[PDB]
Image (cartoon, coloured by chain):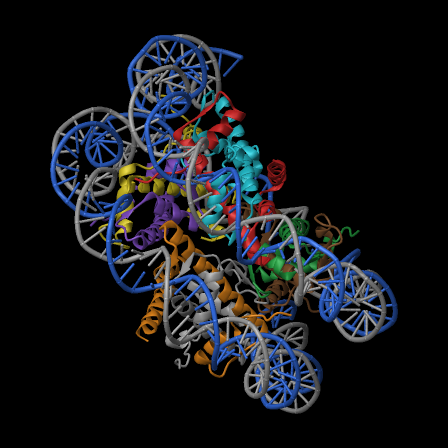
Chain colours: A purple, B orange, D yellow, E green, F brown, G cyan, H red, J blue
DNA sequence: ATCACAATCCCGGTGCCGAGGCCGCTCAATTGGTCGTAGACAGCTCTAGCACCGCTTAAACGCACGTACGGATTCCGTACGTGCGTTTAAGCGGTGCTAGAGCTGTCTACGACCAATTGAGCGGCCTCGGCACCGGGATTGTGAT
DNA sequence: ATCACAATCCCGGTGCCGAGGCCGCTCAATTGGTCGTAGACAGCTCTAGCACCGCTTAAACGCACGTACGGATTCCGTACGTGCGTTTAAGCGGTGCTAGAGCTGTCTACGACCAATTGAGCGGCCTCGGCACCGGGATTGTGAT
C-alpha cells in the first residue's frame, strides 16, 4: 500500500516545467498548488482509463486505454497508437 | 405533413410522479425534449465506440452501463447505474 | 389465439418507451446488432435524469410562487446543482437568464 | 567570486528547456504516483510500460500549458512572479 | 446591399449585456472592442449554417441549420429543436 | 435636486438584468446585421424567423459569458473598470 | 479471360489506398451505403494534408541541419503554420516540446 | 499474432515526392499514422451526421466535400476541395 | 441618529392567451415461429509485468547572502456615471405577392452480393550511414572597474 | 569603454544502433455478372418569407456637472535567486517467477427477419385557469443634515 508519493514531484521538477512554460520568477506557495492540480488531472484520466480496462475484462492498463481516456476528455495525444 | 415524434407524453408522466400539482409550459417542454435527445446521442455514441474498441458487433447492457460511468459525474452515475440494473432485472424476471 | 400484448416499458416498470428507444438505436448506425437489455437500460437512465431535473425545477417554481415550470426554472435548477451543472456545462438554455451573482469587491463599503 | 544577477540564470534556463524535448519529472517517482492513485479505483492493477509513459507525456504537456496561461495572468497584474491566485484565475477561465 | 449595420449594436445595448454579466464600471473603448468580437462570432456560426443550407440544396436558412452549426462549435443550444 | 452617487444606479441595474431573461439587443438591427454578414457567403439568402432568433439567443449568451470572464480579469488587476486588455486576456486563455 | 487488375488509387492518380479507405468506411458504421466517389475524395484529402505537413517538417529538419524528420520537427512545422495550428489545436505531440517564446517584459532592460 | 495495418508505406511515398533526400524516424512515423487516423474519423463522422440530417442512407462525394468545408480552416479547405474534385474527375474518366 | 425621497415589493381585481383534457385513426410496437451466427467457455502458449540485488554517480536538500520585486501610501487629473431634453427609429398590425419547401409517382443509375484470382502489404533479417558522444577551440554575452 | 570570466556554439573523429532495402507469403483488392432499391426528377400545392405603409410612443443621443478611480511616484522590508557542500535515491543491468492476454475449436443462447394484429401516440378542437397588466399602499435602502 503506497502512500505520500505526491512529494516525489519535487520543487526542482516543478521549476523546470515552469521554465519550459516561460516563467521567470516563482513564489514559494506555487509548489503545493501545482501538486494539487496535477493530482486532480491524474485522478480524472486514470479513472476513465481503468473504466476502459474493466470493460475489456482485463487486469492490465494498456497505452490504448490511456489514449482513449485522454481523447474523450478533449486532450488528444499522438505517439502511442491513437 | 408527416407526423412528428417527441418525448413530451413521457416527460409529462414523470412530472406528475414527482410534482402532482405542477404543470409545464410549451417552451420548457421544448427544452426537456432537446435534453433527452442530447443525452441519448452522448450515451449511444460512447457505447458505439466501446463496441468498436473491443471488436464486438453488438451493443448490450454492458456497453450502456460503461458509457454511463464514463459520461455522468459522481453520484449521478452511481444512482443511474442502480436504476438501469433494477429495470433490466425486473424485465428479465417477467 | 395469441396472448394480449403487454409493453416492454411496463415489463421493465418504466414510463419512458422501451420499444421506441430500441428502434432509435437500430436506425442510428451505432452497431450491427442491438441486444435486448440495451434499450431497457437506456430508457431507465433517461427517465432517471429527467426526474432529477423536474424535481429541482418544480422546487424552483414553488420558490418563485408559480404553478407552471418555465425555462427560467430549469436554468435555476441546473446551475444551482453541482453535478447537473457539470453535465450540462456547455449548454445554453434559451430564455434561461443567469444566476444572480455580484462580486464582493463591487459592493459599497 | 563571480555571481550572476538574479534573473540571469532563470532566463538561461528558459532558453535551455524551451529548445529541448525530454521529460522533466523523474520517471520512478511518477510511476509510484500513478500506481498510488489507481489503487482507489481497482486493487492489484498492472500497467504496461508505455501506458505510464503516455500518462507522463500528457501530464507534463498539461502543466507546461497551464504555466504559460499562469504567466500571462501575472503580467496582466504588472508582476513578473507567478502566485497561486494566477493559477486559480487561469483554471477558472479555462473552465476547469 | 446592406452596409454598416454593426453600429446598430448600440452603446446602451452593450452596457445592458455587461450588467447581466455583473460589470459595474465600463471604459469608453469597450464598445468598439465588443462589436469586433461579436462580428467574429457571428461570421463563424453563419458560415457553417449556410454550409448546411447549401448541402441540402435549400435557399432558406432554418433554425435547425443554426442549431447544428452551434453544436459542432461546442456551443449547444436548447430550445429550438436540438 | 436628488442625485445618486456613481455606482449606485449601476449596482441597481446589475440586480435588474440578472433577475430577468429578455433579450437585450433590439431585434430589427440584429436582423440587419445577420443578413449583412450572410451576403458574403451566398447571395439572395432567406432566413426563417426562428433561425434569426436562435442566432440572437446564442450571441447574447456568448457575450454575457465573456463579460463575466472579463470582469474577473479586471478584479485580478485590482480594478473595478473593464478595459480592452481584459477582454483580450480572457479570449486568449479561452483559446479563441 | 478477364482484364488484368489495376488499382483504384492508380485510376485516381493517388498514392493513398482507395480500396482500403472504402473498406474502412464500410465497417465503421457510418452509413448503410457508401458511394464509389467517396473513398476517392477522402483518400485525396488525406494525401493532401499529409503532403503539407511533411513539406513544412522537412524544411524544419533542413533548418536544424538534419537528414531525418523527428517529432520535434513535426511540432515546429505545425505550431509555426496558422491553419495547421488551428486544425491540431487540441493535439499533444509526444516528444514535441514547445515553441521558443519569452514574454518581452521579462527581458533585461 | 494477427497482422497489423498502418499508413506508413503511403506516408513514405508522399515524403519521397516532396523531399527526395529526407528520411523519417520511427517515432515520427507513429505521429503521422495517428494524424491520418484522427482526420479520417473527423471527416467520416461529420459525413455520417450530414447524411442523417438529410435522411439519406448513402455517403457520397458530396457529403465528403461538405464535411471538409466544415472541418478545415480557410485556405486548407479550398485546396483540399480542389484536390478531391480533381481526383474524382480523373477516376471517372478512366 | 434623522428626515425627505426615489425605487421596488406586495396586494387585489380583470382579461386573456396558453395549457390541459378529449377523440379517432393510423402507424408502429408486440407476438410467434425460424434460422443463423456472435459470443461464451475450456484450454494452451508465451509474452511481458513484477519483485529483487548491486552500483554509479546525477539530482535533490539545506543553508547563507543579498538583490530587487511586491505591496503600501499619497496625490492628482482624467475618465466615466448620472440626469435631462430632444430626436430617431423600433415594434406592431395589416396586406399583398411570390419564392420555395414539402410532397407523389416513376424510372434509371448506382451500389450491394458473391466467386476466383493475383498482386499488394506485412513480418522478418541484414547492413549502410545518420546521429550521438566526447574532446578541444573560439566566440559571446555578463558583470564589475 | 574595458578586461576577466563562465556558458555555449562549433568542428572533428568515431562508434553504434536505427532506418532503409530486400524476400517469403497470405490476405484482401479487383473483375465480372446479377439484382435490389435509393434517389433524381417533373410536377403540384400551400405556406411562410419578403416588401410596403402608417402610427405610437420607447429608446438612443448629445451635453453638462462633478465624483472617484486609475496611474504615477516613493519607500521599504520581505521573499526568492544564486551558489555550495553533503546526502540520497534514480537509473541501469541482470535474473528469476508467474500472471495474464491472445489464440483455437466448439457449442448454445440470443438476435434478426417476417407476417398479422391491435393499441399507443399524434394532430386537431374546446375550454378552465394561471399569468400578466394595471392601480394603490407599504416598505426600504440611499443620501444629505
Measuring from the top left, give residue A53's x and y in whole percent.
31, 51
H60 displayed left or right of B48: right
Q: From this viewpoint, is residue G50 visible?
A: yes
User: Which residue shows up at 34% across the image and 60% down it?
Assistant: B62
Q: In the image, what residue occupies the spot 59% across and 42% down?
A: H73
- Relative to B2, residue B50 above or below: above
| The one of E10 and F78 positioned closer to us in this rendering | E10
- Labels in figure, total: 0
Is D48 placed left or right of A25 in the picture? left
Residue J74 appears at what percent x and percent y?
Answer: 53, 39
Q: Residue A1 location in percent, x, y?
A: 20, 50
Q: Which of J75 and F2 is in front in this view?
A: F2
Residue G74 vertical placement versus F19 (above, below): above
| Quadrant of the image occupied by residue J94 | top left
Which picture quadrant has residue G72? top left
Q: In which quarter of the image is the N terminus of chain F?
A: bottom right
Residue at figure coordinates x 49%, y 42% from the top left? G21
In the image shown, does H38 or J59 lie closer to the viewer?
H38
Q: Where is residue J39 in the image (x, y as percent from the top left)?
A: 62, 54
Can residue E18 be seen at all in this image of the molecule?
no
Amino acid at each position: 500500500v503506497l502512500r505520500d508519493n505526491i512529494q516525489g514531484i519535487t520543487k526542482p521538477a516543478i521549476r523546470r516545467l515552469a521554465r519550459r512554460g516561460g516563467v521567470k520568477r516563482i513564489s514559494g506557495l506555487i509548489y503545493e498548488e501545482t501538486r494539487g492540480v496535477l493530482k486532480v488531472f491524474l485522478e480524472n484520466v486514470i479513472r476513465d482509463a481503468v473504466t476502459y480496462t474493466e470493460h475489456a475484462k482485463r487486469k492490465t492498463v494498456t497505452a490504448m486505454d490511456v489514449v482513449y481516456a485522454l481523447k474523450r476528455q478533449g486532450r488528444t495525444l499522438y505517439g502511442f497508437g491513437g | 405533413r408527416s407526423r412528428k415524434e417527441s418525448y413530451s407524453v413521457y416527460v409529462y408522466k414523470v412530472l406528475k410522479q414527482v410534482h402532482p400539482d405542477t404543470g409545464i409550459s410549451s417552451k420548457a417542454m421544448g427544452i426537456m425534449n432537446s435534453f433527452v435527445n442530447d443525452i441519448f446521442e452522448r450515451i449511444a455514441g460512447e457505447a458505439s465506440r466501446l463496441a468498436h474498441y473491443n471488436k464486438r458487433s453488438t451493443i448490450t447492457s454492458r456497453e450502456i452501463q460503461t458509457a454511463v460511468r464514463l459520461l455522468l459525474p459522481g453520484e449521478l452515475a452511481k444512482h443511474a447505474v442502480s436504476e438501469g440494473t433494477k429495470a433490466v432485472t425486473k424485465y428479465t424476471s417477467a | 389465439a395469441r396472448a394480449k400484448a403487454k409493453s416492454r416499458s411496463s415489463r421493465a416498470g418504466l414510463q419512458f418507451p422501451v420499444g421506441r428507444v430500441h428502434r432509435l438505436l437500430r436506425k442510428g448506425n451505432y452497431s450491427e446488432r442491438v441486444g435486448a437489455g440495451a434499450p431497457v437500460y437506456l430508457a431507465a437512465v433517461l427517465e432517471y435524469l429527467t426526474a432529477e431535473i423536474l424535481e429541482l425545477a418544480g422546487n424552483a417554481a414553488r420558490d418563485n410562487k408559480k404553478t407552471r415550470i418555465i425555462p427560467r426554472h430549469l436554468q435555476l435548477a441546473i446551475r444551482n446543482d453541482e453535478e447537473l451543472n457539470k453535465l450540462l456545462g456547455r449548454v445554453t438554455i434559451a430564455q434561461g437568464g443567469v444566476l444572480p451573482n455580484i462580486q464582493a469587491v463591487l459592493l459599497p463599503k | 567570486p563571480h555571481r550572476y544577477r538574479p534573473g540571469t540564470v532563470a532566463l538561461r534556463e528558459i532558453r535551455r528547456y524551451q529548445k529541448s524535448t525530454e521529460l522533466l519529472i523523474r520517471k520512478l517517482p511518477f510511476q509510484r504516483l500513478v500506481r498510488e492513485i489507481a489503487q482507489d479505483f481497482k486493487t492489484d492493477l498492472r500497467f504496461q510500460s508505455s501506458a505510464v509513459m503516455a500518462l507522463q507525456e500528457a501530464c507534463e504537456a498539461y502543466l507546461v500549458g497551464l504555466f504559460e496561461d499562469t504567466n500571462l495572468c501575472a503580467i496582466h497584474a504588472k508582476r513578473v512572479t507567478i502566485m497561486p491566485k494566477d493559477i486559480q484565475l487561469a483554471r477558472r477561465i479555462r473552465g476547469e
